Image 1 (cartoon, helix red, strand yellow):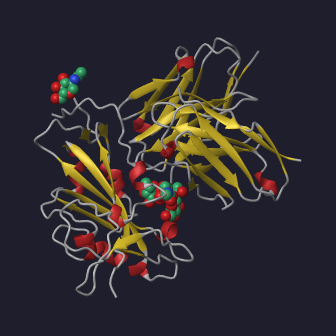
Image 2 (image 1 turned 90 degrees about the horizontal axis):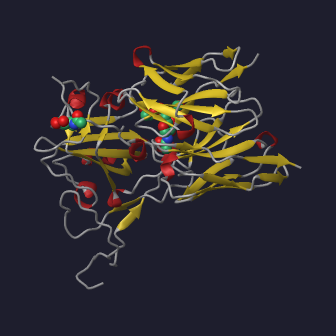
Length: 118
Length: 108
Length: 202
Ligand SMILES: *[C@@H]1O[C@H](CO[C@@H]2O[C@@H](C)[C@@H](O)[C@@H](O)[C@@H]2O)[C@@H](O[C@@H]2O[C@H](CO)[C@@H](O)[C@H](O)[C@H]2NC(C)=O)[C@H](O)[C@H]1NC(C)=O
Ligand SMILES: *[C@@H]1O[C@H](CO)[C@@H](O)[C@H](O)[C@H]1NC(C)=O
């Protein structure tokens, strides 16, 4: 019954910051890992990083160390990613994905485009 | 690290025939963490295969995954008109995800 | 207070429970779980299991515990054979394929797998041992291919010890296949490594 729900976005200037939320439903927020994946136009997918809320462990992909913050707030069954100091090379679709333990199946949300421009 | 490479980058196929996609890892992985996905332009990835072989709910039995070690594959038995899409493999172990570029399965 | 080990991982149970292929009963598959966190509430609360019986522990207390080791033994049996996977039981599986010690700590979990394991013409990849000269000791795997007797002669007779089952959609419930996972625990006198989801403090 797992579902991931994401918000929309727009940024008016490079150097600014976007924070995107992913609300989880269907229960089992705990005992799961949440990852963020980006898809730039014309590209394939890349992993940015991810978090395990009950261990409160965050692991970032190396190219995204700096600028990217991944956090979570289990009290509202949600997770966030924030990308600061945007450079317009990053006007990609951002997806959240979740996997529970006791399973193998990966659930995906509806990726949200973050467009950054004058 | 774990780098998946797909082959061929592109396919040119008749609707109605059989075709396969290859995915090759740089280092061996557990089969339990491999998945195949597809996209149509403008859409979120659709899961087809997980655990390197289980079929995802809602996926027709045209799609069959298999493999081990570094060598994995996805077979589509008939290539129906709806099956022409960009496909790709993913390794989803807990420490690092990797996505395999992708292959474009064209009709022509 | 709550003062559990500084564990940085979630337990890899998906591989145990959500696998496409399960071992046959005479060649059951054991896996070890260690140095991880698991929330047992979720699995327990799921309504998918037909059987969930614990020995020495209660399901509701599992999250407050931490174990030395956890071993997961998985295999396929018929529905009517579920009765035998328990301490104190006898029968062709309890005696020839999968023996539990009678003094047992852990949980036995099982569910109907007709949708995955039965095949239209019969899934004959699942075999059971019918012939053995003596009973098994706890946790033995008899994977031999030796041949058994009938009359008082050397090797009418020469029975192949294993029998495949016709797991087919045509079966009534007692003949549908079931997937069984047994979680065996080691605990207390130990530097325990498999812990529940507790908020360790101070
Ligand atoms: C792999 O797991 C999926 C998901 O199963 C759910 O989560 C489990 C932890 C457990 O609580 C299950 O009972 C839950 O359903 C399985 O997909 C489900 O399969 C059943 C048929 O048996 C179907 O009725 C459900 O709708 C499916 N749910 C979803 C979300 O797809 C899948 O069958 C498992 N695969 C294997 C090989 O075991
Ligand atoms: C790890 O956990 C044990 C539990 O008894 C504790 O003694 C030890 O100090 C902990 N290590 C750290 C770095 O906190």
